[PDB]
Amino acid sequence: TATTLFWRPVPVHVKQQDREDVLEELTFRILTGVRILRIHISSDSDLFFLHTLEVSEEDFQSLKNDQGILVDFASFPGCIISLLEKCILAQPGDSPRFQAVLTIRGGESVFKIVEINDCKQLPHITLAFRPG
Amino acid sequence: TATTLFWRPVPVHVKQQDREDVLEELTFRILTGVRILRIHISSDSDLFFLHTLEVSEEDFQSLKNDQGILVDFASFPGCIISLLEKCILAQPGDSPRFQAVLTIRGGESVFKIVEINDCKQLPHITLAFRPG
Image (cartoon, rainbow over all chains, first blue to last red; front, top):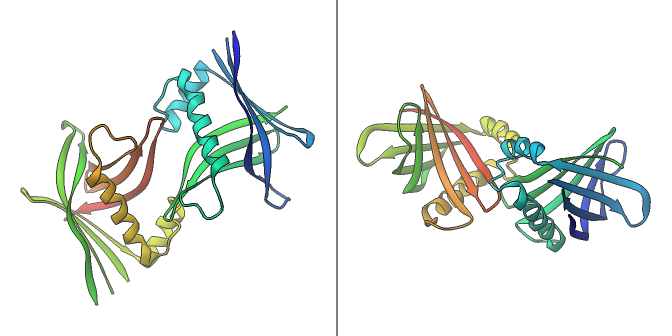
């Protein structure tokens, strides 16, 4: 009555005030179970770099209305996974390029996946994480 | 010291309160000259369906900051034209599909081009037009 859908490294542009922007390989673990969706971001080299998201079906309706999400809750993790794969596969010089960004705030972070083409940067998903 | 860059029909989903949604072939004429950008939307069958946008270099900096536009003013019309072409070429069943939408308000309209994929609707450009 629970399953891991994804457990892989992803290149993430980490942004934190008072620090230089860096690109880090961060591990994402996506779990579903009884319905909830849980995502953990960790670092294979920093035991205390830990960020978690937990979304219930209810919370999802909110997300769904704000970001033009067109799928149901059951299919949402697949949307996230397809975006993360585009981030993993992006190469220098690519256009369009998908990039993952994690902005660190006090007690909360914002994870987004954006598409950068020759004309515009477009957000595809934006999600709130908390430490731990 | 002036030039037409585009003069072609585009399929547009026209939305107006108190009317049913319709899909119309509307003619777009894009002009540049001395710098300004002018766009006219018309209908080959309704002499009084007329909407115009005029953008100066100054107005563009505003647009540029709000919608993540990554090009300079000189290259902006090409961005619009590339989006309009995707709308023209979209076929039933396509995914992703680009669609053009014109929402009619009192004395102003909003033109947008959106991308619809299996997961999300994404706006690529949003522009204000006025009658005439």
